[PDB]
Length: 144
Length: 145
Ligand SMILES: Cc1ccc(CN(C(=O)N[C@@H](CS(=O)(=O)C[C@]23C[C@H]4C[C@H](C[C@H](C4)C2)C3)C(=O)O)C(=O)c2ccc(-c3ccccc3)cc2)cc1
Ligand SMILES: Cc1ccc(CN(C(=O)N[C@@H](CS(=O)(=O)C[C@]23C[C@H]4C[C@H](C[C@H](C4)C2)C3)C(=O)O)C(=O)c2ccc(-c3ccccc3)cc2)cc1
Image (cartoon, rainbow over all chains, first blue to last red; front, side, top):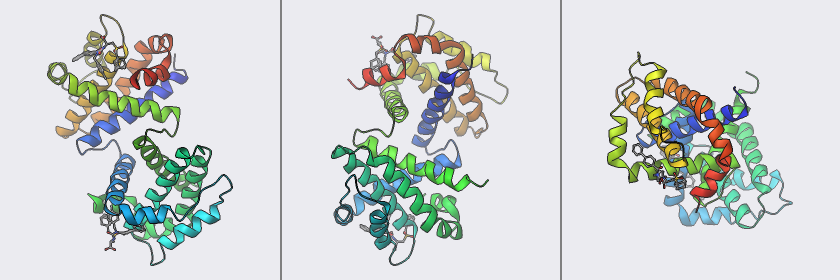
């Protein structure tokens, strides 16, 4: 019978197939294609701007009392000269480094908080620009 | 829909953060850890058994006319002598190679059908073994040492 294990097994199938296709330059779906391009873009960005990115991550002193306001202020400096795809990649890489740092410092509780901050920032600040500049599909075209 | 951006942007955040955490040996969730261990196990298996795996994948070529039974027949031979985690990894890798081949042959439509055959096989055949052998959490523990 179709219980809860069948649902989680389907999720594993989709994830594994998405991975294998991506290794050959193919994609499970357009969403998987966006996820893959953004994973690779973040790696490329972190490699190209290692030293300058280290200076950015050091600007936010994450503690269990850190509110969205503090994250928004640092991220706003990133988009000071306007929005572009590269600055959006830097934004994802920044939230990415904050999560790693939180777990390193045994503050795993902050990971869910960071994820919610990122979603709010995207929706409030970046989504209108993303829509006006061809959506995530254009980012995939440009990156590939 | 009213919640479509909220859903998709959240999905992107979760995916990217899961990826960054995994690169440093951490995991977003227990499900993310299962997914990562299975991705790495698949790569390991494919590397260790390159020649034997080539013999297996050459047994089946999916066309728009291929029925589930042809897939189930080949997969059944993987588990004729019993189930273990390594044979489960080989099953996932097998499905992955069938999907790659479908896209190589410009038949991307078959990838969702293969994924549904894999889910059916797991539900109809492997759930009792997975449960009895400690679930996917035991696979993660065993693979990680
Ligand atoms: C993968 C990647 C590679 C490079 C960059 C570097 N960069 C730019 O290259 N900026 C371009 C404008 S752009 O449209 O963003 C160009 C893109 C080229 C391809 C396809 C698509 C996504 C990627 C990769 C960027 C467009 C410019 O100004 O000439 C930047 O926008 C940039 C952003 C942030 C920092 C930075 C670094 C450390 C602390 C704070 C900020 C530096 C450069 C960012 C990502
Ligand atoms: C990542 C990986 C590495 C090796 C194998 C090879 N292998 C075994 O090594 N089998 C073990 C028993 S086991 O419980 O599967 C051991 C595991 C060790 C770690 C942690 C966890 C998942 C992985 C990796 C296997 C348990 C044995 O027999 O002593 C096999 O069971 C095996 C399965 C299928 C084929 C095969 C090859 C080509 C065409 C068709 C089938 C060959 C060997 C499969 C995966």
